[PDB]
Image 1 (cartoon, one colour):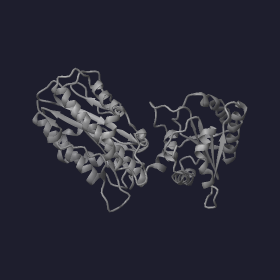
Image 2 (cartoon, rainbow, N blue to C red):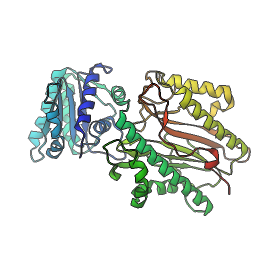
Image 3 (cartoon, rainbow, N blue to C red):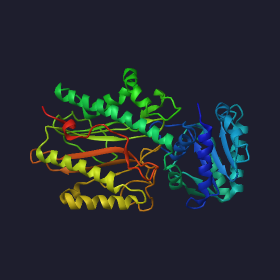
Image 4 (cartoon, rainbow, N blue to C red):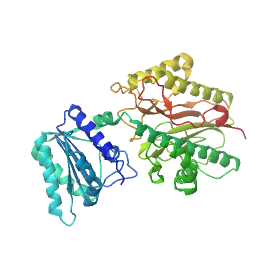
Length: 444
């Protein structure tokens, strides 16, 4: 751990200053982190750790009550956090930080800690704010679960969801966050370059390889230390001032996806299939590298011996993205207003494609890959786009008919787009790997 505690103090203060105005008016907040799960990394409590500390702290409880932050954790972790206590000790602080150390040879001490924090919460009032979808396992949780359940039943706690409130508190990216998002996005560009190269070779060398094995080839390159060394200059250059670039901090947002031949699925649920790579028509590729917990996403369509209608529809896909980012994706507008405006545009330029279009044009991106309270569809009329928002702008058309094949085709484009904090400045593409038709088309 090398923790910026000024950033910690800063984000804790922002939270504490917003949370009583969260829906339902919670008197206190409670985050409980079991064991970490690499296969389930975007739970709110984990996102909270990441925003506060840039690390996930397992077997750790954090409570926000009026005038006090309580952290129940190991001795080891309490030493990592110790420098924080002093930082709140000063009279520009409405809040004190307390570290309550667990002792695993002392089970009765440990139970006491839980009883004591629940008493503090009860004092704050009856409404307790917890991320309702959080679901952690392991030994710490098994200690916690019965104690908390008994507390709710005996103390008449009104336990309410705070997911939307948390989503709002950390939505806007500060300069350092924007820079980590830039690094993460450059990593996406690098892996997509490799992906395109590898996909072209697999077609050229007639490789026996499925869509899934090819995307797995790309996925595992994150472990190739030679490959990582190649990436480092371009990525490290983008790191924020005073921050050194670190390999340990580079990860996947999700497993890479390659689609070809028979099956195109434009839903976020899509996975690479076990079908042999199909070296003709449209190839959809998605990469999304994470850096220092900050997610990105890029999606490209490659055209292998396209028909004229395919190539034409690809040109429209480019013109559509340019319209959205330049003219539609504006601060102050809701996801619903943005989406309706997109449909309207397609209606006045290529009306017949409307039924084939995706039901969203992406979501807010950040420490969470896909914020469910900020999807760019018609169901969200309750968020406004803000300066400092980063989006995964991702859309496509599926089930497009190819006059030349029994296989329908599909086209898909995704980029990570930053909205600057400055009013005078336009949306900035963080992913910049080519999407020019002549550079993603291949003839065999």
